[PDB]
Image (cartoon, rainbow, N blue to C red; front, top):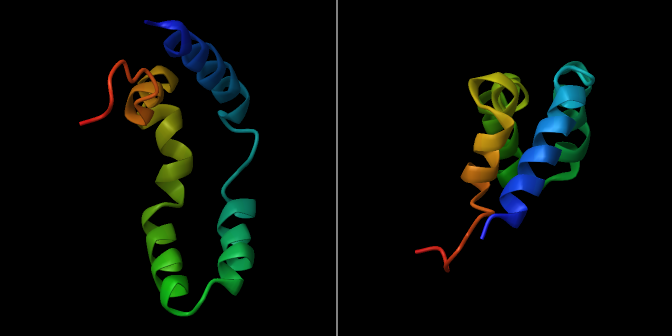
Length: 84
């Protein structure tokens, strides 16, 4: 009833300790200029538009604006029943 909740808190928290700031946002926003480079045109505009919306936060959000344990909740991995 709480096996993955702990494993998801010990790993998502330990990884955070290293993910905390091991990779900056320079190789990220650039990566998008690479993977989101072959994306079709339509979804390449929504993939670069969202990046601006998911670039400095997405990387700085799971880290501080949020705690590693909460993520396990947002992810809903402790699903005891079938999600409604």
